[PDB]
Length: 122
Image 1: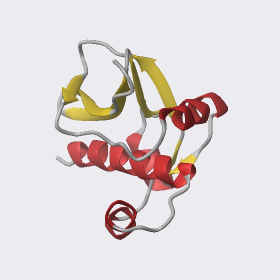
Image 2 (image 1 turned 60 degrees about the vertical axis):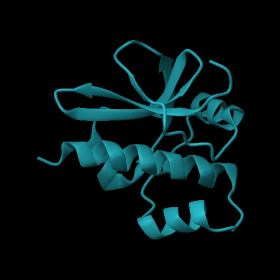
Image 3 (image 1 turned 180 degrees about the vertical axis):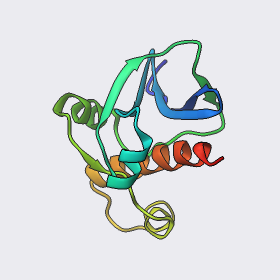
Image 4 (image 1 turned 120 degrees about the horizontal axis):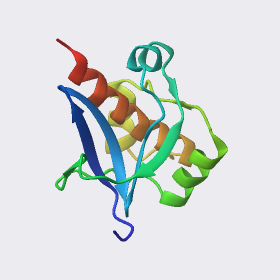
């Protein structure tokens, strides 16, 4: 609960919602419809109160952006591209090209969506 950005997930009957824990709050994609989010490749973020339902991945953490920018994105209701493929993610995380705050948040949003989408595959 001090500027730490850890990956966490909420598991309801095997379907997983992923989010970023900062303090006593969770940032996640504002969607209960993963079909439409995935098909459109677009989402905004929301911030909710952390609860015991959330499971922290203490060895995972997405430190790609400053939290204030994500707070601003939540407040502004900005709609991000969350459909980057592995090549784009790989270039972003293993390369040295400039990465805007919007691109950085879109990257983390892609990771959240992809992780949640993979949990749906029956």
